[PDB]
Image (cartoon, coloured by chain):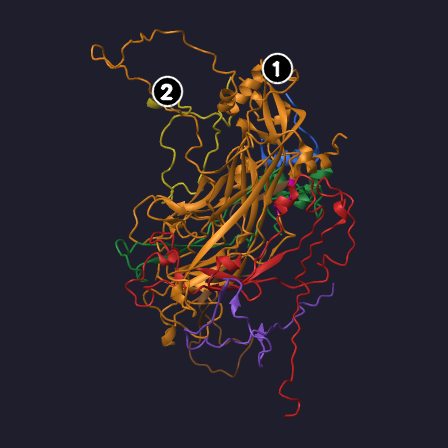
Chain colours: A orange, B blue, C green, D red, E brown, F yellow, G purple
């Protein structure tokens, strides 16, 4: 009956020439780069690392309750209003720089880049190894939260023995604020796929490194998870290393380059095969101000999908990764006594701190939706919460009923009147953690007064009135 | 499928050729 | 420096076959050495209970996962098979006519 | 502020170990209402991590004994080598790469036609501030002196 | 028109042989070396990048 | 007389549906478009390709 | 990145500007004497190219 074939927002969402500016004052966060400091439960210093997803959930004021002076341009009997994102800027405050991560007890046996002689094996051959991760910048903007992908442990079709390889599955999830980006060790669930707990650095050893699923996010029907994205990523292999442990899969005894069997029987030292489980340390090379995605205005003229920047539900999700400002600052405190004249290593407590700084600025265009029967059916099939949020659907089905209102409710001559049951049950995205930014009291029509606003005015021609 | 705009490549092909789907 | 995740519009081919998918077949040959991340995963199979790290304990494995998604835009073309076109197609590849009719 | 944040006095090289390293507040200078603090700017920054080191000292926050310590999680308590963790306070040695004549910001005329803010180049108060950093000509010349006499062979 | 989608993150994987035929490093050798039976070594490398 | 439901109908199809470690054959319950003649045996004749 | 050898012309002042404190390695039998703080780099004009 109603329709098929998802149509562009440009067919039922009519723009106006009213543009508003909205921005955040300045968003700072200070933490530890590797792990959250707790006492035993309450977080004393959170984990703030330069390799996290920053997923900002922006809240817009409902444009249907805006008190415009002459409202004669829209009819609230048959029309409703929405915000459309037209300009954005993701400001970034810290200097450029590269921070490193490591593990005090990393599962690395040797260096196999160039071995001067053949090697050995004992118990606990773990080493203290640090590395700079892959360089990554990305920005995604949409009205729904982003989708990320990672490889995880699946249930096998039969039972296995103790120590067998876990089967892989590609698992889609929402990307949340504080999720780790891929760092060059892949998109994988380190908590479940590596029971060693020593296979990758400390900031990811128990995390799930996720990558944005661009393939599923562009190929969704309405195009709401992202309507713009930019990305830059670079990596090279810095050093080439070996694992230690019981070899789970042996090398096949047949050599396919020569078509023969091979064993080091003639050489006593090489008879026990060295580990063929290799890993490289990643390295994101030279960071540059020329390569920068951020601190630039982006004008969203034509979206990638059928949602041409329409901020349905008065919500917007801004997902940022910036591995270009991951400088971890090394703090030290003089403990015990501020009196010694000689350096001791026991006299100073070393600490690590990371500080991020963001500033977000947007240009929103007001748009009007005239809610005819087919437009109502199409919006209802697309998303019912749109026509619930905007008073119009759910015309009132029942009639009145007596509640009998017992005068003395706390007396023992009547039955118990307790009822009062419902706590508020609204938020469907409550299980997810985002950097919630409130822009309800931050909308302004004076574009000239703001840096992105006057950039938008200059780009569109539109000089201020004299 | 002949409904080109429904898919990411198909609406990229339409945007490239002009050829926009008729607004209903 | 990526070649992939981009649409490529075949406006004109290199040779005399201007994109014609003879026999209802198309070959797509991809090599991509920029996503060759081998995921090193271990298991605690010989190690339920121990609170001290041992090497005999953990079994190490290697895995790799590829992901592809191929999208195309095909155009319908018609060929009117006269004596000259039929003989020319038979000279090019007899299997084309043997698969159709004529 | 290296002076008040690092009482070790040995965490960064001599020229900055007692100083304050500042970055220009582009976000604040741009969002100033009149646009007077800057009306034109440029920048070229670059760095790579050259070497990766540790810090010696008493550990301030111990690594938690769960999956937050990574490889140092699984305590090597059975092994006399790795019972006590190495310091997990890593610092990278920076390196600004190859300086080139092509990438030079300076020795080029700039024409201030349209400023960033509302102040379009008006030098209020008969005054102007020009802020320059040029780390591409930072070569320190080595001098020597033959103090004990040029006489001996 | 055609498009080849690629889903995984970017990255370089390395491979090697546990018993690779190398005798010595010749990029910079301090002095003359030696040789015997089975001088094979465990050696890994990143391959040529190709798309 | 049916619009697309707001959920979508993206199916997740594995290429090797008999392998261990992928959860199930995934399609045990016959929810959608089962004729009530499931309980009856007929000489089923397909003429789809015979018109 | 190298050092120079010779008598110190100007010694490092007794105060450490990063920590705001005086410093000396008088508690150790190695660092009691400062190493020469006269550093010099060796230049390198990289790849010469025909373009």
* Marks 2, 1: nearer the viewer: 1
- Mark 2 and 1 residues: CB-CB less than 8 Å, in contact? no
Observer-nearest of E49 and A298: A298
Q: Say if the magenta span includes residue A176.
A: no
Q: Secondary structure at mark 1?
A: loop
Q: Chain of mark 1?
A: A
Q: Which residue is mark 2?
A: F36
Q: Residue A353 or A178: which is nearer the viewer?
A: A353
| Chain that bears disc 2 | F
Mark yes or no: residue F13 visible.
yes
| In the depicted structure, whether residue D106 falls above or below residue A166 | below
Q: Residues within 10 Å of mark 1 (few under 14, many from 20)?
A: few
Highlighted magenta segment, given as a residue range? A293-297
Q: Quadrant of residue D151?
A: bottom right
- Relative depth, front residue between A30 and A229: A30
Please tell me how crowded label 2 is: few (under 14), some (14-19), or many (20+) other residues with Cα within 10 Å. few
Alpha-carbon span between mark 2 and mark 1: 51 Å
Q: Is residue A14 left or right of residue A58?
A: right
- Magenta stretch, main secondary structure class: loop
- For label 2, the SS is helix
Residue A369's disc is none
> What residue did someone put label 1 on?
A75
């Amino acid at each position: 009956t109603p329709v098929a074939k998802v149509q562009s927002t440009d067919e039922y969402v009519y723009p106006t020439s009213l543009f508003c500016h909205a921005h955040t004052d300045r968003l700072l966060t200070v933490g530890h780069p590797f792990f959250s400091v707790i006492d035993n439960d309450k977080v004393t210093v959170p984990k703030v690392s330069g390799n996290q997803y920053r997923v900002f959930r922006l809240k817009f004021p409902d444009p249907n309750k805006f008190a415009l002076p002459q409202k004669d341009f829209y009819d609230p009997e048959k029309e409703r209003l929405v915000w459309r994102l037209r300009g954005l800027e993701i400001g970034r405050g810290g200097p450029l720089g590269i921070g490193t991560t490591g593990h005090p007890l990393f599962n690395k046996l040797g260096d196999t880049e160039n071995p001067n002689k053949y090697q050995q094996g004992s118990k606990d051959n773990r080493q203290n190894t640090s590395m700079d991760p892959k360089q990554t910048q990305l920005f995604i903007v949409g009205c729904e939260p982003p989708t990320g992908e990672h490889w995880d442990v699946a249930k096998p079709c039969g039972a296995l023995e103790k120590g067998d390889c876990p089967p892989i599955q590609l698992v889609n999830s929402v990307i949340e604020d504080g999720d780790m980006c891929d760092i060059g060790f892949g998109n994988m669930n380190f908590k479940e796929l590596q029971q060693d707990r020593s296979g990758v650095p400390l900031d990811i050893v128990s995390t799930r490194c996720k990558w944005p699923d661009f393939l599923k996010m562009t190929n969704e029907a309405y195009g709401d998870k992202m309507f713009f994205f930019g990305r830059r990523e670079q990596v090279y292999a810095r050093h080439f290393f070996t694992r230690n442990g019981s070899v789970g899969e042996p090398i096949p005894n047949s050599v396919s380059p020569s078509d023969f069997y091979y064993a080091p029987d003639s050489t006593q030292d090489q008879k026990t095969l060295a580990p063929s489980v290799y890993f490289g340390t990643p390295s994101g090379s030279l960071v540059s101000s020329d390569g920068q995605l951020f601190n630039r205005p982006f004008w969203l003229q034509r979206a990638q999908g059928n949602n041409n920047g329409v901020c349905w539900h008065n919500e917007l999700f801004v997902t940022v990764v910036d591995n270009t400002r991951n400088t971890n600052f090394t703090i030290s405190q003089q403990t015990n006594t501020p009196n010694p004249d000689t350096y001791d290593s026991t006299n100073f407590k070393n600490y690590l701190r990371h500080v991020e700084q963001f500033e977000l600025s947007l240009i929103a265009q007001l748009c009007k939706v005239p809610l005819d029967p087919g437009v109502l059916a199409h919006i209802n099939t697309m998303n019912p919460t749109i026509l619930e949020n905007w008073n119009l659907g759910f015309v009132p089905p029942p009639q009145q009923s007596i509640s009998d209102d017992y005068r003395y409710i706390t007396s023992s001559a009547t039955r118990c009147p307790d009822q009062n049951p419902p706590k508020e049950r609204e938020d469907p995205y409550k299980g997810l953690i985002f950097w919630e930014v409130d822009l309800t009291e931050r909308f302004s029509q004076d574009l000239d007064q703001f840096a992105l606003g006057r950039k938008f005015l200059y780009q569109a021609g539109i000089r201020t009135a004299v | 499928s002949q409904d080109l705009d429904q898919f990411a490549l198909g609406r990229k092909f339409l945007y490239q050729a002009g050829i926009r789907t008729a607004v209903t």
